[PDB]
Image 1 (cartoon, rainbow, N blue to C red):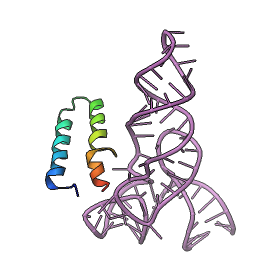
Image 2: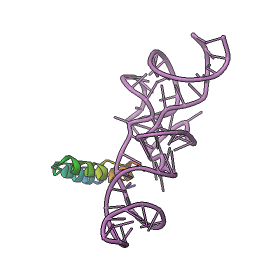
Image 3: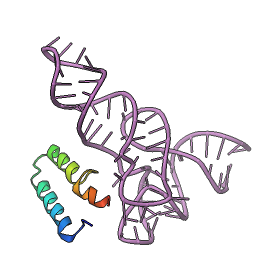
Image 4: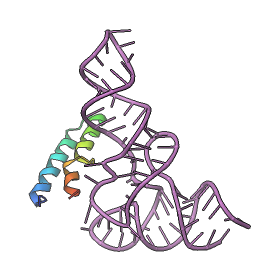
Length: 48
RNA sequence: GGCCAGGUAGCUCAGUCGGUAUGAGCGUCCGCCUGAAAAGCGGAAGGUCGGCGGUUCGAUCCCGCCCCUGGCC
């Protein structure tokens, strides 16, 4: 099982950092697809 | 008024009685391509699955109410 507490924290810390570096709404939409869509790292985690 | 059957992507519709709708066709975007296009080929974006709540670690799928189409009245 690859859902350790430091595994999800590695994804959230990388997601919130990219969200913090989103300066326009178009960039945020691209970040949303990579960190909250059905192909995000959290997606493969929640799919298991 | 009854037990049902339906509301799902921009359009027209499939599909699942709990952890991915690997959704389809067409519509939208990028690349190869063309003077520029389209087709073709190869990549992608986009749905809070009818609304408000209930159960649950987690609900398009299970409970209750309501909204709107139909079938029978």
